[PDB]
Image: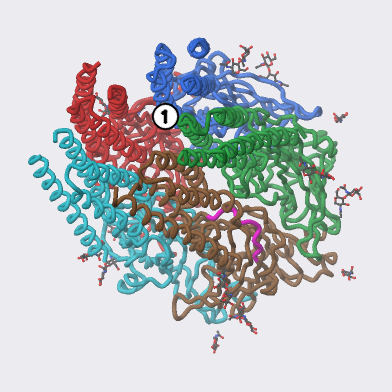
Chain colours: A cyan, B red, C blue, D green, E brown
Amino acid sequence: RPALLRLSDYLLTNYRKGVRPVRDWRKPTTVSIDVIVYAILNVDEKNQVLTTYIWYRQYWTDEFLQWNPEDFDNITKLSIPTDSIWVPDILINEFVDVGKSPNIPYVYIRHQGEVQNYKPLQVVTACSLDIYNFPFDVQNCSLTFTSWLHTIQDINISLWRLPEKVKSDRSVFMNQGEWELLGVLPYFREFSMESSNYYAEMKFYVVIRRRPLFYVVSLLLPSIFLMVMDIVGFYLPPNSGERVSFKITLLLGYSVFLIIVSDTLPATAIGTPLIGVYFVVCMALLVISLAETIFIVRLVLRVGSVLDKLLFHIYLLAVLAYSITLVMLWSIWQ
Amino acid sequence: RPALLRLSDYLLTNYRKGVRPVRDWRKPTTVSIDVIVYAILNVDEKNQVLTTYIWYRQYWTDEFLQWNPEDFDNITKLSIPTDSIWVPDILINEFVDVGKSPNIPYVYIRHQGEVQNYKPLQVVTACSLDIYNFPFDVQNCSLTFTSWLHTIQDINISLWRLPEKVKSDRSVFMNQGEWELLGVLPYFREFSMESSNYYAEMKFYVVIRRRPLFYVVSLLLPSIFLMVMDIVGFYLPPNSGERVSFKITLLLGYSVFLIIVSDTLPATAIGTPLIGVYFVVCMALLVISLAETIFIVGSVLDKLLFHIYLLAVLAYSITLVMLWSIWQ
Amino acid sequence: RPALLRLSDYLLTNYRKGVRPVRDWRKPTTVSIDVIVYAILNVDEKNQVLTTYIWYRQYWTDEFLQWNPEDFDNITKLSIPTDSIWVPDILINEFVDVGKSPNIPYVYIRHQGEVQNYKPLQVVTACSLDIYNFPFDVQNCSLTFTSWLHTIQDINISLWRLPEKVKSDRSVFMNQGEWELLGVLPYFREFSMESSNYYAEMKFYVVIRRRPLFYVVSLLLPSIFLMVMDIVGFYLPPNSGERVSFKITLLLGYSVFLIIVSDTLPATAIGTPLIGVYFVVCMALLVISLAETIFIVRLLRVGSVLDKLLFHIYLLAVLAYSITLVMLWSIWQY
Amino acid sequence: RPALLRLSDYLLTNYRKGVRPVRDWRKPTTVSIDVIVYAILNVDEKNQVLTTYIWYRQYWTDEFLQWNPEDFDNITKLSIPTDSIWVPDILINEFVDVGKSPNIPYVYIRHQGEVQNYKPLQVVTACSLDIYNFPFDVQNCSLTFTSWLHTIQDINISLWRLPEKVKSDRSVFMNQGEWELLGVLPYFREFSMESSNYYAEMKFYVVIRRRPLFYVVSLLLPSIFLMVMDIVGFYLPPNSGERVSFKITLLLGYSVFLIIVSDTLPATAIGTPLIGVYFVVCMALLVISLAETIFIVRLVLRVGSVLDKLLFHIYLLAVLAYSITLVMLWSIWQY
Amino acid sequence: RPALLRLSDYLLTNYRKGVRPVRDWRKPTTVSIDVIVYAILNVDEKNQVLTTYIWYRQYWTDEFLQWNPEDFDNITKLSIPTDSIWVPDILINEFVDVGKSPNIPYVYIRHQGEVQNYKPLQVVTACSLDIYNFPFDVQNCSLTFTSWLHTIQDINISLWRLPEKVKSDRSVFMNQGEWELLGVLPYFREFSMESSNYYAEMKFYVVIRRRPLFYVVSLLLPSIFLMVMDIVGFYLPPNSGERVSFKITLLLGYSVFLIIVSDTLPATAIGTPLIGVYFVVCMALLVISLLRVGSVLDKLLFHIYLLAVLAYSITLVMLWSIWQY
Ligand SMILES: *[C@@H]1O[C@H](CO)[C@@H](O[C@@H]2O[C@H](CO)[C@@H](O)[C@H](O)[C@H]2NC(C)=O)[C@H](O)[C@H]1NC(C)=O
Ligand SMILES: *[C@@H]1O[C@H](CO)[C@@H](O[C@@H]2O[C@H](CO)[C@@H](O)[C@H](O)[C@H]2NC(C)=O)[C@H](O)[C@H]1NC(C)=O
Ligand SMILES: *[C@@H]1O[C@H](CO)[C@@H](O[C@@H]2O[C@H](CO)[C@@H](O)[C@H](O)[C@H]2NC(C)=O)[C@H](O)[C@H]1NC(C)=O
Ligand SMILES: *[C@@H]1O[C@H](CO)[C@@H](O[C@@H]2O[C@H](CO)[C@@H](O)[C@H](O)[C@H]2NC(C)=O)[C@H](O)[C@H]1NC(C)=O
Ligand SMILES: *[C@@H]1O[C@H](CO)[C@@H](O[C@@H]2O[C@H](CO)[C@@H](O)[C@H](O)[C@H]2NC(C)=O)[C@H](O)[C@H]1NC(C)=O
Ligand SMILES: *[C@@H]1O[C@H](CO)[C@@H](O[C@@H]2O[C@H](CO)[C@@H](O)[C@H](O)[C@H]2NC(C)=O)[C@H](O)[C@H]1NC(C)=O
Ligand SMILES: *[C@@H]1O[C@H](CO)[C@@H](O[C@@H]2O[C@H](CO)[C@@H](O)[C@H](O)[C@H]2NC(C)=O)[C@H](O)[C@H]1NC(C)=O
Ligand SMILES: *[C@@H]1O[C@H](CO)[C@@H](O[C@@H]2O[C@H](CO)[C@@H](O)[C@H](O)[C@H]2NC(C)=O)[C@H](O)[C@H]1NC(C)=O
Ligand SMILES: *[C@@H]1O[C@H](CO)[C@@H](O[C@@H]2O[C@H](CO)[C@@H](O)[C@H](O)[C@H]2NC(C)=O)[C@H](O)[C@H]1NC(C)=O
Ligand SMILES: *[C@@H]1O[C@H](CO)[C@@H](O[C@@H]2O[C@H](CO)[C@@H](O)[C@H](O)[C@H]2NC(C)=O)[C@H](O)[C@H]1NC(C)=O
Ligand SMILES: *[C@@H]1O[C@H](CO)[C@@H](O)[C@H](O)[C@H]1NC(C)=O
Ligand SMILES: *[C@@H]1O[C@H](CO)[C@@H](O)[C@H](O)[C@H]1NC(C)=O
Ligand SMILES: *[C@@H]1O[C@H](CO)[C@@H](O)[C@H](O)[C@H]1NC(C)=O
Ligand SMILES: *[C@@H]1O[C@H](CO)[C@@H](O)[C@H](O)[C@H]1NC(C)=O
Ligand SMILES: *[C@@H]1O[C@H](CO)[C@@H](O)[C@H](O)[C@H]1NC(C)=O
């Protein structure tokens, strides 16, 4: 019979999945995992979940699937169905849906007993997505692979590659998209909330930052244009109907702009972005100034002049704060 | 042969899944259970369901999976596939969808026959959600685990931990989110719809309250500002065009505010919050005042409508104080 | 050996599923059934479907799963996996999707052979859902259970309980919700698609009615407010500018109310509700009234009689609307 | 042992599913099929797919599942699990989802070897749903059942009932709905992806037509009402601000009408409905007439009067064409 | 026993799925594949996923499933369940969902050992869609098939048909739809995630373009009508009520046009559609009303409007030109 067929028979007719493959039960099975991010398919700041398509590969030593290549025509490694052998139950804690990814029927066995398992994960995980810096926003999400049942005495987890490689690896990442990732940071720890159970878990912090240009052109530049134009409402003659008409029309322009803002901004219930805070503050200041003009026009002057200067100074202060905040947010993002 | 392999063969060679594991059929199988809420993924007040991600673990005594460690290299406990042993039919009654949780292949067996089963559940359950206090909600609805088929003299349920410990347990809860849970309250009862049969069930009341600050900033403060502006608007005489122009400005503000609210205020079919009632009442008063001004430009109507407006704002104000008081 | 273990072996090592469990093939298997409605999750008038959560239980006599208790330590009842025995193919015809229900691994067996099977069903079924009486809706559609393949000479269906007990059963219904059920009505008939075969089917009519209060407050009362406002307005002089102003302002308000209704009224294409038709009619009648004043004021005996005719016609329409509301409530209350 | 049990053991003990049940491999397996449409659950003119709940039943001769009734207590037929026997891979083309139908565990076997398989299919398939005639629209969507792998040398398809009996079959159709079906027309043909292989397929053309009354009431009557109001508006003099205000309010009525209609007028990208074209052309005519009126007001006249009458005539002609196209669409929809 | 039954018995009694079917393990298994696009079911730019329903067929030589026809009643070909034999793990990369593909129980075997597997794939894949030219879009989305686990030393991929034939093949495409595909371009390369290992993969570039006529009728012509009317309205004086009435007329026109737009115009965060910005810009500019200063700001505004419309026209011509060729 051919080498592959009789080798597979030799291995799997004696093998019995369902028992951790160690001939000394005190020895833990060390699962060396690795993660390569392929694409951040989706990021719901509304639902506080994100969908990451990651190529996940892990290997472990199976002490029963060993053979001498000299007896089997120099076969160094062979592929066998994944469901035919014991597979560690490594699982990611913050999953929200098991995922719609395929099964990848096969795994590789090397004559040393090492089992290599490559599988794609279209995992969607709960995440603390915060849009406080909306346009210049950097999200720091994490994935935590942990042996769900087995304690560290049974299954331990480690990195396949050196940490420096996995941090900087962006070989196959789909760069085009709303998000670009700066790196995935591994971190090992012995999770434990129990009297005598310590579970090994491997955290990967996937750092991703939004690329703002579309939002810069859509929100920031028009908002800056409107805020700059609003300064002119304070150089037109103080109580003229011309000035009141100007302020009314620019308030209408701001109001219609905020509709586009509502359309464009991502929905959330955790916290409003600073951009929205400044927009609504400017709207309130403009309304107050317009009301002051309306009232003073009803009356009329000295009070009007001093109030006008006060409102102009507060408006200038607000717009300066907004611009400095934009610069600061950009500095944080880069 | 290695101890693990021959121990597994010894246990499972003659084992027969599908029979309740007791050597005296009169004894009930007591399934001790525990629940830890990991995250409240979604609360939907239109579909009246909420999705919670919970770490559910349970253990029971399987009287056939027993061995002396002396014969098996002092193997005190081992893991074997979950599908290879009898597993109790504990089910959550008010589930709406089975969920998308994984299968968790293995379970632990201790040499005394105790089987420990840990499994994550993304349960989606029906609940009597109400948004009467929308920004200051405190929802309170149950998860009840019961043996679906087996009566109490076949399967019985109990708590793994003391009730107070599970009640105060928030070790792993994912805090950052719209909902924070005040506690889960266990409660045991013998359900029955026909006297010949009694069923053991264990209710867990997950108590969660919305953290309002986002809606305080986004909804309450702009509405308060607009109400204050409309109140000040009445200092202009009705016979003055300034008043109608100012009213138009505030109606434009309310249009913008309503559009923003549409993106945020929850939809439902059972009833809107008091906040919505006050919103529409204030908008109606503003519109009626605009009609009054455009009609004038009956003078006592000015101060009458102003008093109604002042009354509404005060009612709106004390409602917020009351709702906040309940929220604490 | 323990009693349960050897009893289960004795039964299921000889037993073979697939074959209908009857030792005389000329005898049909009578499958008693029962249904308890747990909740009405979703009634969709756009898709013309509704989703109900029902606790469905059925029992039948299996003539091979019988034993003498004396031989098995007086075991008079035991549980065995549902997939280890013949399970009748009782299926629901109106189904549109099987649903998200679990599988309930086990069933009960009594020593005389009767098998008890309990299973929850998330049935979603096609139904003719008309909203003609929208606020005071009462719906009438049904669920029919029938052996999909087997004729009545193989499988016949029957009620577990007396018809009046299932009819009045509201022991577990989730009452808090948009819909309340008035009862479930069983009805047995021998369906026959082709003259050579007869099939047993058991129709359950799940009668439900909407609880209107939210829609009564949200739609009906504001609508009547607007309509009575128009009636009040008709008191103004015919050619007066006040009359035209009132008409046009009420047009704006009523149109925005129609927009609100569109936002709130359920979507459908099978048919418009009466409430909707009267709204549209009265709007059109108002537009005719408004259009009329433009000609008359532009150009008064003709105006006066024309105004009187319009006023009386609109008042008659208002009365018809109110009487329609009384009729709809009278039907829904009983 | 009981007759059923030993008969089942006699049949299925040595039965080897997977192999086509024919004892002379050269003979094809003729799979007779039938289809009864139960309900047209959803026609999606946006996505150009529809979902039809159809009761599908097929039978074929299995040469190995044969027995002599006298030897087994005179049993003429029995039911056995569907997964225990060879089942032809008759598959519908142009599907978009495998469907949400159950598994129907059992099939009937008759002693001659005929296997009967009844199964409900929640098929969702692609057809070119052209809504040109939207309110009075008749769609001719098709289902084709074909042995996905096996060529005609292995599996051949045929009708269970006479073609006219299936063409006029509405025995169990759920008629209360937006769509009513005029019939399903069978048509056999031998497809050939490459001339070396010939594939037998059975096309059923399900013909369905929208019942318009809802759309009549909600769209066409209000549209006629607004158009008649616009025709009335032309009586007012062009020089009058009354006419300008009337036209502005009528245009606002147009706007609100279309706003509400957006909920019900189907979305699509294959082509605009004819009624939509008339809507937009009347809207544009109204707008341009109003603009000309405003300009002539600015001037304020002979040319003004001539253009007023000309625009009135064009509007009247457009309304006449609208009536003609409505009656035409209705005439086609009747047949 | 009948020929088919005992032939299946001979083949499958000692056959054991799992082992790559070669009697000399050093030989790679060459999986010839072919792909025919049947329909482009969806192009979702908001999620950047494209859904195509494609007829996928592949064949390979299984060196264990061989027989002499003379011994088995001259049977040259037979069908056996797909689950009963080794099947290569040819996986399409950049999938998003495994998809609603049916199981297709059977495959053909020919006495020389060739296995033919036909299966329909409803692949939904993530690829870079863009609506920069919305009404005149042309998209270039890839499908790449690769043996997920096996390296090129185990599984190698090739085309069933000649590249030009598969490229120009549009025999079964559902042509009556929003999208028409120009062709599918195959391309073979040895992917390498590590220096020591090489993976064979086969990219098919599906090239599709939106057919615009609907959007020309629905969007472009009405928008040009409204823009031309806005230009015309400038001749009414800047202080006059005639201009106000004209502006309200135009505003109602835009009110209808924008709901029509919202019902059809796609939106995504990757970038803007050049056509889309003008609509909202012009609708917003009705706010503008910019006596000595006003009368000349009006001419400035008129120049702005005219240049905007000129840019719109040349943009439409450009978009059509890049879409035609
Ligand atoms: C579980 O695995 C971790 C990771 O491999 C082990 O931690 C390493 O221990 C070695 C000891 O020589 C150190 O050199 C490494 O620096 C450690 N790595 C990290 C990330 O801390 C851990 O010792 C293992 N524990 C058990 C019980 O097997
Ligand atoms: C994302 O979060 C991770 C984890 O908190 C940060 O990584 C830590 O950074 C600090 C400061 O440089 C170090 O002292 C820790 O050792 C890091 N942890 C690990 C596991 O490497 C990371 O800096 C954050 N990045 C961003 C952009 O927020
Ligand atoms: C089923 O389980 C319940 C819950 O543990 C048992 O109820 C307890 O019984 C013990 C008996 O010693 C009491 O001390 C506890 O106070 C009971 N707890 C509660 C919450 O009632 C019950 O006895 C078990 N058996 C049966 C037949 O119900
Ligand atoms: C949530 O609902 C539960 C169930 O009604 C409440 O728990 C009960 O509260 C009452 C009043 O304090 C006690 O008498 C009962 O003993 C409690 N039952 C249990 C099982 O603990 C709970 O107080 C509610 N919480 C909120 C915040 O509404
Ligand atoms: C729902 O439909 C059922 C079936 O038509 C109605 O029940 C029938 O009502 C008629 C008239 O009262 C009786 O003669 C039948 O005997 C009833 N059938 C059964 C099985 O009881 C029922 O009335 C409908 N619901 C409503 C609210 O009208
Ligand atoms: C199938 O089952 C139904 C329901 O049990 C049978 O109908 C009953 O027939 C008996 C005959 O005496 C009547 O007394 C009952 O009132 C009937 N019940 C109902 C609900 O109508 C029916 O006879 C059975 N048919 C066969 C062929 O066995
Ligand atoms: C495959 O089946 C079709 C349909 O039954 C066969 O076509 C019919 O064959 C009969 C007998 O020759 C003719 O009377 C009919 O006119 C044919 N057409 C139809 C529509 O019935 C066809 O011959 C079969 N082919 C094979 C190879 O079995
Ligand atoms: C739907 O399409 C079918 C298939 O083209 C039409 O049926 C054909 O009609 C022509 C009319 O000349 C006949 O010559 C063919 O013989 C018919 N074929 C079949 C299989 O019956 C049908 O008329 C169309 N119906 C509608 C309403 O469009
Ligand atoms: C794997 O398959 C590819 C084809 O997909 C082989 O490449 C071909 O090799 C032949 C050798 O004569 C050339 O004529 C073709 O031009 C090649 N095609 C391409 C697309 O490069 C390749 O040799 C096979 N084996 C390996 C190890 O890659
Ligand atoms: C779609 O992308 C493919 C791949 O880049 C293009 O096809 C290649 O184009 C280059 C440049 O003209 C040629 O050198 C190659 O021979 C082409 N084929 C392959 C397989 O690379 C194709 O032109 C693109 N189509 C569109 C419309 O952008
Ligand atoms: C394995 O291959 C080497 C040459 O590469 C050969 O010398 C050796 O004999 C082979 N093994 C056996 C068992 O023949
Ligand atoms: C098992 O444990 C007992 C108690 O500690 C000890 O005496 C014995 O030597 C152990 N046996 C083995 C094989 O470890
Ligand atoms: C079974 O129950 C009967 C009473 O019904 C009793 O007499 C008998 O002893 C019991 N048998 C056993 C083995 O307990
Ligand atoms: C077998 O059944 C047929 C049909 O019912 C009947 O005519 C025949 O007499 C029966 N024969 C025997 C031996 O039962
Ligand atoms: C077997 O079939 C082939 C098909 O071409 C034919 O040429 C050959 O003569 C046949 N041989 C026998 C023995 O039937």
Identify which residue, E285 or E214, lies in the foreground.
E285
Q: Chain of mark 1?
A: C
User: Where, quadrant-wise, is the C terminus of chain A in this rendering?
Assistant: bottom left
Left of D118 or right of it: where is E218?
A: left
Q: Quadrant of residue A138?
A: bottom left
Q: Can residue B11 be seen from the camera position used here?
A: no
Expressed as whole percent of the image width and height from the top left, the position of residue B24 reads 43, 34
Q: How many marks?
A: 1
Q: Mark 1 Cα within 10 Å, few/some/many (few <14, many 20+)?
A: few
Q: Quadrant of residue C64?
A: top right
Expressed as whole percent of the image width and height from the top left, the position of residue E193 reads 45, 75
Residue picked out by circle 1: C256
Magenta stretch prevailing secondary structure:
strand
User: Where, quadrant-wise, is the N terminus of chain A in this rendering?
Assistant: bottom right
Expressed as whole percent of the image width and height from the top left, the position of residue C213 reads 41, 19
Identify which residue, A148 or A237, lies in the foreground.
A237
- Residue at the location (45% across, 23% down)? C173
Ligand 14 shown in quarter: top right
Q: Judge: label 1 CB < 8 Å from ligand 5.
A: no
- Answer above or below: position of E14 versus B51: below
Expressed as whole percent of the image width and height from the top left, the position of residue D99 reads 61, 45
- Answer above or below: position of C258 versus B216: above
**Helix, strand or loop status at disc 1:** helix
Identify which residue, C293 or B124, lies in the foreground.
C293
**Magenta stretch encompasses residue D181:** no
**Magenta stretch encompasses residue E36:** yes
Q: Quadrant of residue C84?
A: top right
Left of A77 or right of it: where is D317?
A: right
Please state the extent of the stretch shown in magenta in the rendering.
Answer: E35-43
- Residue at the location (39% across, 29% down)? B200
At label 1, the amino acid type is: Val
